[PDB]
Figure 1 (cartoon, rainbow over the protein chains, first blue to last red):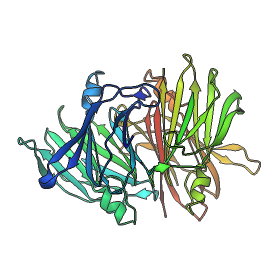
Figure 2 (cartoon, rainbow over the protein chains, first blue to last red; figure 1 turned 60 degrees about the vertical axis):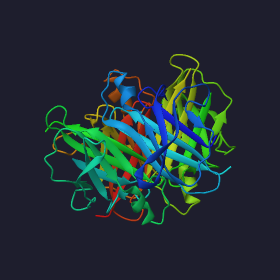
Figure 3 (cartoon, chains in turn purple, green, yellow, cyan; figure 1 turned 135 degrees about the vertical axis):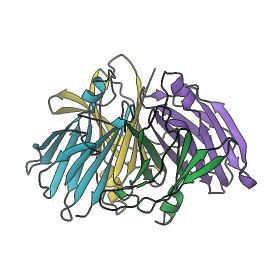
Figure 4 (cartoon, helix red, strand yellow; figure 1 turned 45 degrees about the vertical axis):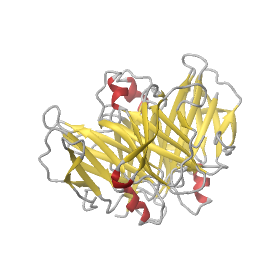
Length: 116
Length: 114
Length: 114
Length: 115
């Protein structure tokens, strides 16, 4: 797939399941146009959310509802959410894996961009 | 509110990194609050503003793109953000530690009791 | 059963032809080879996968990160990257060890399932 | 010349009283002890203060992360966290080793400055 979003819980060492993910595209005038939306689930290596649509050139935003993940576990976390804002600047076809590693007071975000 | 930024490509503090700050408006839009850029002097590896930080959802934007570009690297992210609620239980002491590579970053909050 | 992912944080790609050696602990400062090989990017499996199943115990994963960076004219801080951990304390599990490499930094994460 | 700083990414605080053991490689390729410390938080110095003078050679810093997490009732993934590195290879440097800890994850970074 052209986009893979993985969200990991670094305290449990597991995919963070039932996490809301919202992907957007920069529009003129600052507007963000919704591109994909979904919730994490698991089976095999696919412990994240995949879109089928490829990424033409632009600026994207991935929002991750990490506040609702922790609040479910009895934890009010530092971050109000995780956000990943990036350029898709190879105009030709690229694969994007975006991983978010979650703790109550920390997050980490990593991208892998490959050309198939 | 202290913001410390480390460069994982160079093994150094991230020198001359732009750090902006926002306070949440009623209009769901973000009202500015402060700016700053990380200054390496004596012992300080980060940008510390001189604020009287009240309660409310605050935003920290780090300009990682301009930082990596100026070093001839085409980074992944536009920037690295921390959105958090600052003083929901009296005064608190905040260090945001950010660690930066062209394709990844982590932000950690260190909350001490003043 | 064991997957090791090695990622280049500078380039945002799998770090390929990286040597990985896995060991089982045999006694004080004694390590038995468990499996080994090199990272290879075959699309979606970008890391090293081993057929061998874990029996209960302590395992060491050695990643030759220093060769990887030297082949790039970079003299990294770390001589290698090592992950030591206990396996199968509770039964038959799938382990994915990810290492994210930067010249002055490495970070390691583990996902353990079923 | 050698400083080791530890952050707890679960509790959002310095990791206080984590043990740090530093070894030096020997001409027979073994690990001879070098520096002994648990991490301390007095003032805003949130790490471990190693005093000894650094020569050219290979060093191993071991952070006992398992003891740390077991004391908060968490069974962590890792047995420990180590950094191995060649120090002082181009002359006297100052090392700050920064460790960030969660139970199934950790990172180490070096801040390397010229005195």
